[PDB]
Amino acid sequence: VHLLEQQKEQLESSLQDALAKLKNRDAKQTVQKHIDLLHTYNEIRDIALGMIGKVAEHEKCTS
Amino acid sequence: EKSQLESRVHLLEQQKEQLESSLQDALAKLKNRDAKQTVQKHIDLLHTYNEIRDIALGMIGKVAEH
Amino acid sequence: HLLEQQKEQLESSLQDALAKLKNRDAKQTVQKHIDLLHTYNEIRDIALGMIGKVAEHEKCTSVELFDRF
Amino acid sequence: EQQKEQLESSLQDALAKLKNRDAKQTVQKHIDLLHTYNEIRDIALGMIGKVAE
Ligand SMILES: CCCCCCCCO[C@@H]1O[C@H](CO)[C@@H](O)[C@H](O)[C@H]1O
Ligand SMILES: CCCCCCCCO[C@@H]1O[C@H](CO)[C@@H](O)[C@H](O)[C@H]1O
C-alpha cells in the first residue's frame, strides 16, 4: 500500500501548506499594519507639536 | 456793489464753515468705522487662536494616553 | 480600532476651524467694501457740493460782467 | 495679519498632510485586494494541482 500512503501524504501537505501560506501572509500583513499605524501616529503627534509651537509663538507677542 | 458784495463775502464765510464741518464729520465717521473693523480683526483672530489652541491640546491630551 | 475614531474627529475639527476662519475673512471683506462705499459717497457728496457753490459764484460774476459790459 | 497666515496655514497643512496619507493608503488598499486574491487563486490551484495529481 505505497500508493495509498504516498497519496495521503500528498493530501495532508496540500492542506498544511495552504495553511502555512495563509498564516505567513497574515503574519506579514499584520506586522505591516502595525508599522503603518505607528507612522500615522508619529505624524499626527508631530502635527500637535507643530500646532502648539505656533500657538506658543503667537501667545508670546501680546500681553 | 458794496451791499451785495458784503452778501457774497458773508455767504462764502457761511459756506467755508459748512465745508469744514463736513470734512470734519466725514473724517470722524470714517475713522470710527475703521476702528470698528480693527476691533473686529482682533476678535476674529482671538476666536481662531482659541479654536486652534483647543484642537492642539486635544491632540496633546490624546498623545499623552497612547 | 481607533486608527479611524481619533483621526476622523480631528479631521472634522480641522475642516471646521478652517471653515469658520474663512467665513470670518469673508464677512469682514464685504465689510471693507461696504465701508469704502460709505466713504466714497461722502467725499463725492462734498466735492460736488463745493462744485455747485463755485457754480453759483461763477454765475454771479458772469451776471455782473453782462449787466456791466 | 501675518499672524492669521501662520494660523490658517497651520490648519491647512494639517489637513493636507492627512488627506494625502489617506490618498496613498487608499491606492495601496486597492493593490493589496488584487494581490491577495492572486495568492488565494494560487493556493487554490496548489491544492487542486496536488489532489487531482
Ligand atoms: C468693545 C471693545 C472690545 C475690544 C476687544 C479687543 C480684543 C482683541 O484681541 C487681541 O488684541 C490684541 C491687542 O490689540 C492683539 O495683540 C491680539 O493679537 C488680539 O487677538
Ligand atoms: C522595517 C522597515 C519599514 C520602513 C518604514 C516605512 C517608512 C514610512 O513611509 C510611509 O509610506 C506610506 C505608504 O502607505 C506613506 O503612506 C507614508 O507617507 C510614509 O510614512
Image (cartoon, coloured by chain):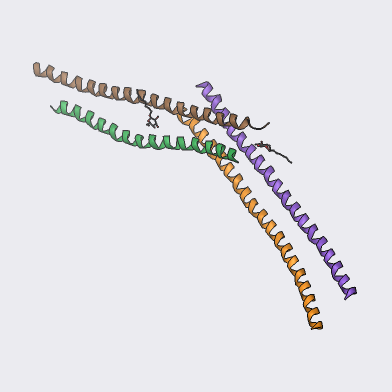
Chain colours: A brown, B purple, C orange, D green
Q: Residue furthest front?
A: C69
x and y percent of residue B51 in the render? 60, 35
Q: Residue at x 59, y 29 (%)?
A: A56
Is A42 displayed left or right of D41 in the figure?
A: right
x and y percent of residue A60 in the render? 63, 29
Is A10 displayed left or right of B6 in the figure?
A: left
The one of A42 and A15 positioned closer to us in this rendering: A42
x and y percent of residue D16 in the render? 47, 38
The image shows a total of numbered marks equal to: 0
Q: Residue furthest right?
A: B3
When the figure is inspected, residue A33 is found, relative to residue B11, above or below; the finding is above
x and y percent of residue C19 in the render? 56, 42
When the figure is inspected, residue B22 is found, relative to residue B36, above or below; the finding is below
State which quarter of the image contains the C terminus of chain A.
Answer: top right
Q: Residue at x 79, y 58 (%)?
A: B20
Is C10 displayed left or right of A31 in the figure?
A: right
Is B51 displayed left or right of B4 in the figure?
A: left
